Amino acid sequence: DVQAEWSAISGLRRHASNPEVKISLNRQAGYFYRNLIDRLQKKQKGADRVLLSGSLLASVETLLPGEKIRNGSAHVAFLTTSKFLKGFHNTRSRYSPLRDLSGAVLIIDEIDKQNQVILSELCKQQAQDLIWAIRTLRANFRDHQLESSPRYDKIEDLFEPLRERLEEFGTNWNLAFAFNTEGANLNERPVRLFSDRSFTHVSSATHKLSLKSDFL
Amino acid sequence: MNVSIEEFTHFDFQLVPEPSPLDLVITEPLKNHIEVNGVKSGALLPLPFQTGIGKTYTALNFLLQQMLEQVRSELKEENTGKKSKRLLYYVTDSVDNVVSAKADLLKLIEKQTVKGEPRFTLEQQEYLKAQIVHLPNQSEQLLQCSDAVLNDVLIGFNLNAERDVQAEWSAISGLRRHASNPEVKISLNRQAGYFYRNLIDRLQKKQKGADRVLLSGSLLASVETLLPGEKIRNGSAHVAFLTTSKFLKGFHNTRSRYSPLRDLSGAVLIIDEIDKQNQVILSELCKQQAQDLIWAIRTLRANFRDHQLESSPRYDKIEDLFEPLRERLEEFGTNWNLAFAFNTEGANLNERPVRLFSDRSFTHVSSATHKLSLKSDFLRRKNLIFSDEKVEGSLIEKHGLLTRFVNEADVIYQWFLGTMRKAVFQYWENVRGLEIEVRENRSLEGTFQEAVQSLLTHFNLQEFESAVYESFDTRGLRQSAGGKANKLSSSKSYHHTGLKLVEVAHNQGTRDTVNCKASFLNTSPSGVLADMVDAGAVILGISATARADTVIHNFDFKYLNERLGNKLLSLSREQKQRVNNYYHSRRNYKDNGVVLTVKYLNSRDAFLDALLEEYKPEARSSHFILNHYLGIAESEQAFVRSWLSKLLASIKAFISSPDNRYMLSLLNRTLDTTRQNINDFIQFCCDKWAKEFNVKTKTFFGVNADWMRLVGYDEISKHLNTELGKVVVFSTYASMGAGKNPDYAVNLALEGESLISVADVTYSTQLRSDIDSIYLEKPTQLLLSDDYSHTANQLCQFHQILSLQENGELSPKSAENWCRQQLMGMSRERSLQQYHQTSDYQSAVRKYIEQAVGRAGRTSLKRKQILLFVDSGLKEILAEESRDPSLFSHEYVALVNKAKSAGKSIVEDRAVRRLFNLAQRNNKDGMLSIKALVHRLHNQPASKSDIQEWQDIRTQLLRYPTVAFQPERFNRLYLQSMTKGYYRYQGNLDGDPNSFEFFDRVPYGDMVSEEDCSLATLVQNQYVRPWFERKGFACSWQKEANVMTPIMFTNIYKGALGEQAVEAVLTAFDFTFEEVPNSIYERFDNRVIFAGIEQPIWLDSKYWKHEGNESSEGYSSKIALVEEEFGPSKFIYVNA
Amino acid sequence: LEIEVRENRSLEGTFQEAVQSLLTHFNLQEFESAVYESFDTRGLRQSAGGKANK
DNA sequence: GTGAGGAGTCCATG
DNA sequence: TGAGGAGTCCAT
């Protein structure tokens, strides 16, 4: 598979003159890297650690310029704000600059405009179904237990209040059932809610909505 | 213009062309089948045909007649009832066959005439040509459509506003225009496939209610062009042409993906080359995802504890289908402490993984030096895997075993899937009838998807959607109340049981936990075909070698003939005679002067070394010439020398012929540029031999698929009818199976005045010819293998081994040895060595030879002398054939007759060996099943299934000692015997089951018959005789060739007879009997109460003065357990 | 407290192993993607400063 | 009618 | 140490 994809990309590379090859070339060069780097990282994880020396080290460094930081060859970098908030790959895994900033120097030009970039990056978070997550957590946090070893010391004590809270929540809100809408005027338009977690609350309905539990 | 059905109002629907004898063989068995069984049934009918006579003509005429009958049924319809249109399929294994078949059908529709007058008009032809569709893969469908169609489709659904779709479409459109260089094609194909997937997904998700865009006008035509499958759903067309893989996968319409294997009621299926269909089905079944058993079990146990379903009329009679699964999950969770993770312990376990294999019935192997256990520690919160002790463990196993864990996990998983399928069926049944609401499609597709989602959402879960959607296509036709059940009270076979594979190793990243992957295989292609016929479907299969005796290269007709029953239609003798006469008339080789010459060739070293010393004079010895000029090393010289000598002998014998100008060689290897030295050797040898006797010779090198799709096979035909000389071509067995038709037309000027017609009354606009010299090499590598991944190969090998064991060609000892050696690791040569000792190998070789010689003559203009050259290893085999020689072509009979006229030795019949092996297998299965059932019974009873099975087996064995016909329900309790009524045997009933012997080989062994049980002296008592007639028992053993197995004659029958006799004699007097409770089951016989003395009493019985040699400690323990159960008691031991 | 095997490294090195171990032990493996996006030493995607709405 | 009144870009994933 | 090779779908 790797040879097939590499051969296709290499053949497509040799005719990158007219301006319709470029778009496809970029869009598949964006997918070759993921598979190649994933295989390279998985191979080096726990077994068959192939040593790096000679021209092989130079080739890997040329393919992965972020590798030179881990060994210590270079300690100065140039990159943009979008790449800064994501991280770069090395032979082991991805390295996030924001998780370690002790003793560093940052130079930013046009610092004011970075607010918009950070706002754009913060607004791509994926959504989540609350009912499914709460029910899954309530189900799996009932009997399962952790190990008793020196490497797992003073970790269980951090999960007790969560267990005490989840069972009370489930008993009070009847999470053994599911949810559905009843009555007219609620089947043609959805319901939307908004809150700022402190004191601002708005609703998208004329009247207030209530929840009920039916035992039949 | 849009034509309609009204144009057929004035048409003679009774006038039909004159039938042919080949066309009368199909219609009469179907007419008889309709009278016998009914209108709603299935049938499998293999038709042995040949190249030459019009197979395609017959099939296409059948299709056309079906279409016309549908038109007739529609004309007198819409006034008395209404129903959907019947579906007709044409399935093969290659695209070129589909294209050619469609073109031939269209040409036949256009150009058919009757009584000198055309059968159809223009409007009728145009209506008939609009009922057929062709469904290629998703990559070619996108490239077939034009820009306007996609533009209108995008605009109509309002999808041009998006950015990703527009960019991808722009990229594809830009790349398509310059699709001339052979470098941009592959990326174009891949991108087209991905874009088609995304576009179809968006279109399907848009039309899920809400803003359902109405289809009419140009938009409808464009959508139908883009999606040919919508025509079937709306009702435009009802005839489809497609390959096998697309049939197994499915196709798309504007609502969902339609699987053709879910609704076969009705339908007609025409299949060509059914053996390759078997192989393709097997290759498809081996690609499937694995599963982590621990994760699935802990998820099901967690999410089946509190969550509940809704109590509405829609969801009625569904919740009661899940209680046993919940109870079993609770018991499984509490038994093995599923609140902790799993980990290994000790050395020698992290070095290599642990692998386990099982056939689910009686075969188990393990790649572990010692048995591995499972222990639970309450101070570390873990479950540990340890090897105990090397010397037999130094104790008794009381901690548990891994194999039991794996088996119960698999059982629970399969149970869950089956319960889901049943629940969804009940949901559709409930929804369709009542609850008047918006009804659009009252069928099994939309209800299928809605039921699956609704049932999965209520029970949380939602992670098993893929495991349920991809498991319906195979497992939804099971549960036929006897068709698939693993019990001693039901039919058992490998073809609906399967196998299993498990691997245990570390996780990713973590160094404290382990997982258990599992790869399954739930059925075989024979089961798939049987389920296709069982659901109701008419299947027609055309092949010259349909009923062969290979289970590896064909289906298993012994299983199909035992499952289907009367639904497997077969021809009669007179129909075969008519077919033979029709073939003879058009291939009347005799009465004209056509001869066939057959020779067998051996090797000769003097020939070869004289050749090399004549063409390499500067060298000293032949060996040095080989290593230097030709390249063969010293390790593998003899093989090359022998093969080259055998080839050169045939070539030299062919060249020295006056009136022959064509010859092809069928080898096992390709003589490409990698063997240029051998190519040059053969080239100048042929050049010298052509200079000896004055004639011109041309040699063709490298006939491959890559050469037949880049240069063309018409070059050879063109060179023959324009120039003079001889041509010799080199090909392989597999390459000649594609493309076909090696014909050159005519040139009378260059002909050698020798060409004779063979037919009786024939006139043709054009004339052709065929080959007149063939050399055949012995086939090699006759064992299946898979290149997709690594697990598929193992699955295929285990499937082949288990199929061979079930058929009867292998004993259980060899099967277990082969399975163990394969699990540990084997080479290909050692795999072929063990296959070369069976009877299927010769059948496969013979079938390959027959097929190779069958595809050489397709015309009726032949030459007077035909040369056939064969090897000697083939001569060893071809002399052994005993069948009906009616439809055996003309070259095949010559080969067999020439090989037979040499004497040779005799061959042991297959039936004797098969009987011995089947008896051994039945004994082994019975032993293991009985032991497992007894062990389960002595634990907590759980009642229901186990007690009922025990009593049913006892009653059945009491009623029928011997049966006349082959049983269908309990087939693992009887064996076939050479002598009727009794048989001989020897062996140990408490040791290795692979050490038994039967029949002739043991003339001094023990005996199973009517006299040994002494039933004659047991019926003479006055208080026992009427009991037998009251209960319907058998007072004598009827003489039939099916008797109880040795295991079922000692451990079951005697106890039942003794218990019945003691019950009769005691009930004759003033006594009472009852049944024992659950906890004391199998530890006593019954309970007796009389005279008001309660003092609970139990008794035991023995048929004879049996000395069980059981220690008094066990009896004392049983008595103590009984006492502490109740208290004071009395016990009685009775001999019968 | 262990130093049984020589690995050295900092919190950035032994970060995937801990998450995988805890998630495997607690039978919550569908939350792996959601636990990496908002993960760091402390915060950077979940509040800041006082870290208390009181 | 009544508010006001448009180009430009970085990167990841089949 | 026995045996000693090409050909072909379809989807993500």
Image: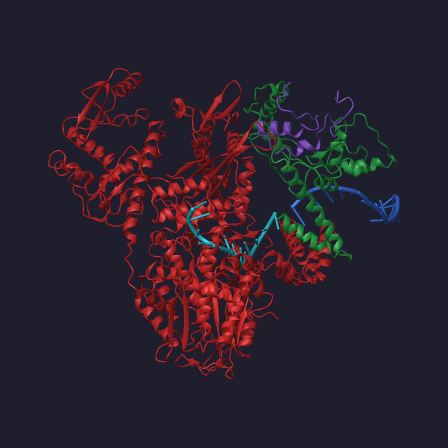
Chain colours: A green, B red, C purple, D blue, E cyan
Image quadrant in which the C terminus of chain B is located: top left
Closer-to-camera residue (B109/B1052): B1052
Q: In this view, does B463 lie above or below A12?
A: above
- Would residue B181 be visible to someone looking at this image? yes
**In the image, what residue occupies the spot 17% across and 32% down?**
B1061
The answer to whether residue B801 is left or right of residue A122 is left
Residue B935 appears left or right of B172: left
User: Which one is in front, B573 or B462?
Assistant: B573
Q: Residue at x 66, y 54 (%)?
A: B213
Report the quarter where the N terminus of chain B lies: bottom right
Query: Which of these two is toward me, B561 or B800?
Result: B800
Say above or below: B319 vs B644: above
Residue B1077 position within the rendered picture, expressed as x and y whole percent measured from the top left: 30, 25
Nearer to us in this view, B371 or A102: B371
The reply to whether residue B477 is visible in this rendering is no
Q: Quadrant of residue C31?
A: top right
- What residue is shown at x 50% (from left), y 64% (from top)? B612
Residue B717 in the image: x percent, y percent? Answer: 54, 74
Q: Locate residue B262, reporting x and y percent.
A: 48, 51
Judge left or right: residue B1021 versus residue B334.
left
